């Protein structure tokens, strides 16, 4: 859990 | 729903 690539908040594909 | 900022898959804070 923390920063880098995976699932959660930030940039990429999903909702917003 | 799509690409940009928000939640889901890609780069930022959460789970790897
Ligand atoms: Cl797109
Ligand atoms: Cl942006
Ligand atoms: Cl949120
Ligand atoms: Cl946190
Ligand atoms: Cl994970
Ligand atoms: Rb993410
Ligand atoms: Rb993300
Ligand atoms: Rb997004
Ligand atoms: Rb991560």
Image (spheres, coloured by chain):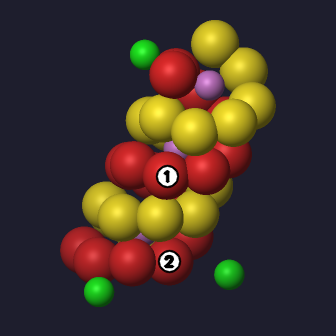
Chain colours: A yellow, B red
Q: Is mark 2 within 8 Å of ligand 8?
A: yes
SS state under label 2? strand
Q: Is residue B3 above or below residue A4?
A: below
Can the viewer see residue A9?
A: no
Same subunit under labels 2 and 1? Answer: yes
Q: Which residue matches tag 1?
A: B10
Residue A1 found in image quarter? top right
Q: Please tell me how crowded label 2 is: few (under 14), some (14-19), or many (20+) other residues with Cα within 10 Å.
A: some
Which residue lies under the disc numbered 2?
B4
Measured in 3D between alpha carbons, the distance from the residue under mark 2 to the one under mark 1, in whole angstroms, is 10 Å
Whether residue A14 is visible, yes or no, is yes
Task: Classify mark 1 as within 8 Å of ligand 7 or not, answering yes or no.
Answer: yes
Q: Nearer the viewer, residue A2 or A16?
A: A2
Q: Indicate the chain on which mark 2 is placed.
A: B
Please name the residue shown 50% across and 77% down the image. B4
Other-residue count near label 1 (Cα within 10 Å), few / some / many at <14 / 14–19 / ≥20: many
| Chain letter behind tag 1 | B
What mark, if any, has residue A9 been given in the picture?
Answer: none
Identify which residue is drawn at 39% across, 49% down.
B9
Camera-side residue of A5 and B14: A5
Tell which tag, 2 or 1, sits nearer the viewer. 1
């Amino acid at each position: 859990v923390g920063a880098x690539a995976x699932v959660x908040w930030x940039w990429x594909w999903x909702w917003x």
